[PDB]
Image 1: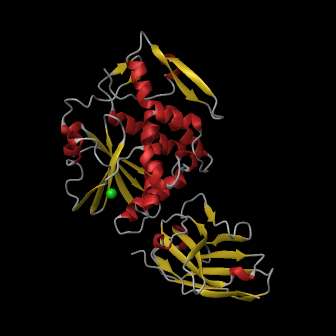
Image 2: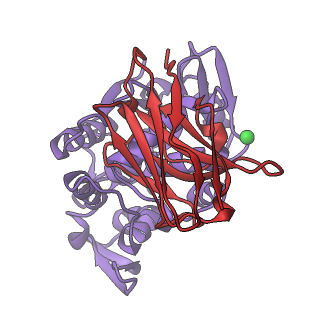
Image 3: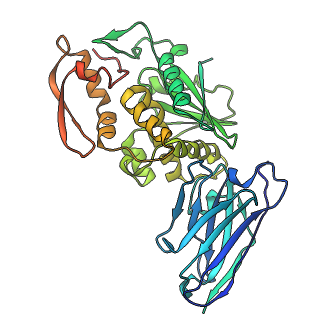
Length: 129
Length: 255
Ligand SMILES: [Cl-]
């Protein structure tokens, strides 16, 4: 099928103004590589619900989408030789604190909707203080 | 059954897409039927069912595929098939209703939307005007995917409407207008996506009125001017078929 395993990482505690880099690493031996996929990045606070932040399409033209909240601070990017997609979170502040998720769909588009991806990472906590 | 034109967004080129649109045009026409030098689509009235439709099979780099059905009379998308499922825009009447029952006869799941495929409706559902929806190989690549995933619940309505708007314009409007075909070529050439400007939109809007003006014209002169817009939204009028020769490739039957 489209079966793929997404292992994220790179989260943790950071001083306000600080920066972190998240990683969605696709595990080996999925039929398709990660570049065939659209990858969404979501974040969820405990009392809140999932929220889309940054996204990158499967499209060959590299289209990316960014929610107003993170625009210009966050940058989504690809490394294909490592079968990986990075999220660089800069100028971090406490309001950013939440658990972050990576999500993927084969041949997908750049969406802030959780329904529009088929596969999820385990999540990684971010905290800014 | 109906003829099929294949197209893939994967490694698509200007030549790739141009051959596709020509092929598409070729299948709509021709009865050697040309009024004032513009080919005319077959007349809906009396048209046998088996000449009614053409199919367009689209696939992307992810090997996802869908097939669009176009009515040869207007060159407009009436619906699509993906695997086990087929969806149709709401027919304007019972003649068109009956007609579409001859599409995708093998498909095990048939669905007909409560809404039609006109822009006004689709823009509402997309949450955006054609002005704000980008076109190009990428947007089309995604649209194929969005339609493919729709039956399994992986596609939000706004995303579907948006995907229809992309297909209609990059296939139907492109076939209707060499001018629109060309705007798409440019997007593919530079591998960039962009939304259409007023010059594209007013054309799309005016395809029916131009069809009429041309076929009901006097020796090519329009009984009344048709007003269009330029890229900056400035208005101008078309008084004659002559200037539209290079512009519009097809017309719905009138008279
Ligand atoms: Cl419906």
